[PDB]
Image (cartoon, rainbow, N blue to C red; front, side, top):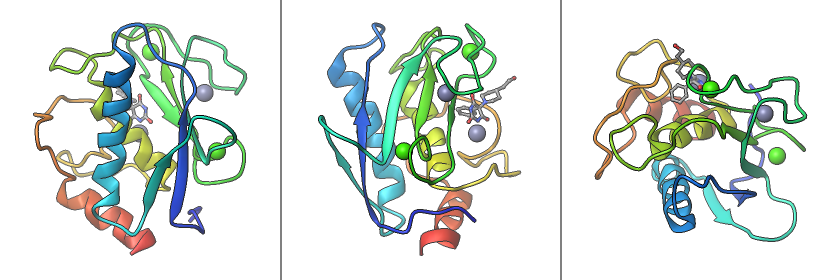
Amino acid sequence: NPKWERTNLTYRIRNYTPQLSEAEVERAIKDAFELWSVASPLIFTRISQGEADINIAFYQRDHGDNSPFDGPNGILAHAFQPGQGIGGDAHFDAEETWTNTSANYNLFLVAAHEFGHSLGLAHSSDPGALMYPNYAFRETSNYSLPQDDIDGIQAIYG
Ligand SMILES: O=C1N=C(O)NC(=O)[C@@]1(c1ccccc1)N1CCC(CCO)CC1
Ligand SMILES: [Ca+2]
Ligand SMILES: [Ca+2]
Ligand SMILES: [Zn+2]
Ligand SMILES: [Zn+2]
């Protein structure tokens, strides 16, 4: 069970996607981290300089980590289990259409799912859980962590 030994973690947005404004990308990420924060003792702090626990970036095909992206559709992003260096980091496929609406693909939703991986959660078998191994849009306004996911982080961090 790889998990963070610390509760205050830092994250850093290394690059942005041209598809949305910087503020939009930052808002999506912030909201995505908040989902998890309200159900655990984890506190996330955004940094702009230096080394952060969770590095977030948009990359194309080969990007230096044994898991190149596949272009439009297919895998949308990937994250690393809690750990030093690359651990906890999340990479988003730069070739995907990134949105903040119902159109594929909503960044807030994909990001929330990736952060679950970054936190140590595995995939869930419950089709209504954020951690279910498939992307499906759900109303983002006032969206909150589903029941199963709350049980998930809870089981790890309390
Ligand atoms: O389950 C996933 N888990 C990821 O970490 N990354 C993905 O892209 C993932 C994902 C799921 C949900 C949200 C974000 C990402 N997913 C997207 C849909 C795809 C379906 C191929 O038909 C299977 C891999
Ligand atoms: Ca892809
Ligand atoms: Ca890291
Ligand atoms: Zn990667
Ligand atoms: Zn996943």
